[PDB]
Amino acid sequence: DLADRFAELERRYDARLGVYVPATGTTAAIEYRADERFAFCATFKAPLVAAVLHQNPLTHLDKLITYTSDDIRSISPVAQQHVQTGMTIGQLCDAAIRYSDGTAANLLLADLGGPGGGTAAFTGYLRSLGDTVSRLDAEEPELNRDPPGDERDTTTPHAIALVLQQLVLGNALPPDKRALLTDWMARNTTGAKRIRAGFPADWKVIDKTGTGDYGRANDIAVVWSPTGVPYVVAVMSDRAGGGYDAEPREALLAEAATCVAGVLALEHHHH
């Protein structure tokens, strides 16, 4: 029946929807198109920050990066305001996650893999985590613009949720670094109408959104019940039928999340 509900969302929104919630010790996996490829869009920025955190001491967060107006080739709310004074690596991580800053992402990719080597190094971080499916091939803003079906710049709901699980809920990061990642996601500003909108206010939600051409709208989150039980939620979507300038529809993601939350929150007392 949950598959029937997701199918109805696809019809109503003229969209392709992918959902993955990993199984837990007391909940079955929720899977819809979970092995189909979808463009990451900005969702890669959460693992990207992880990779930078992992490979460096915390003192690397204080390193000041200078850039110019010519580096700003993508929507960059925070980099545009510090272009004259520069941004530390920590500031860039913050911006990349909380404001989906494109320049910040590109600077972090340069810090991880050097000029021209960022996308391969980022992909390499995913492979170190055991993700053999995802791939990043372009920087911002070109990574949001590949046609439908191109495998460049893609993940799957399945792969990205498992990555996030390891980052947030597993041992991929030591606790101090983990807490920075988790806090930046917790205080994201771009996700109010997506997975957050699907969960009750007393569940903690941390997230990272993505939006792109062909009506692409994604969101990846970790949520905790009111008693601290964690679940990962990946929701991916596109609307290729509208062409490259198709309207993304956030509400599809809110609705998919509401379907999930309903399952995760509803209890089944034995009478």
Image (spheres, rainbow, N blue to C red):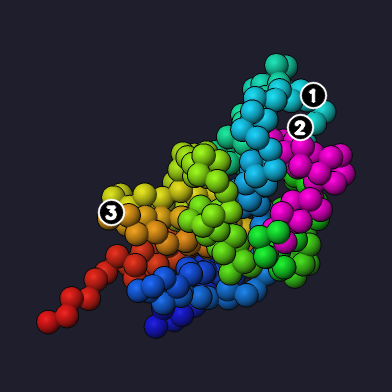
Whole-percent x and y of residue 17? Answer: 55, 69
Asked whether disc 1 touches disc 2, contact meaning CB atoms under 8 Å apart, the reply is yes
Front-lying residue, 145 or 96: 96
Whether residue 228 is visible here, answered yes or no, is yes
Marks 2 and 3, how far apart at CA: 41 Å
Numbered circles on residues, count = 3
Span of residues in magenta: 101-127
Q: Which residue is mark 1?
A: 68
Marks 1 and 2, how far apart at CA: 7 Å
Front-lying residue, 56 or 136: 56
Marks 3 and 1, how far apart at CA: 45 Å
Please indicate whether residue 146 sits to the left or right of residue 9 in the image.
right
Q: Which residue is mark 2?
A: 72
Please indicate whether residue 256 sits to the left or right of residue 68 in the image.
left
Q: Which residue is mark 3?
A: 226
Q: Helix, strand, or loop for circle 3?
A: loop
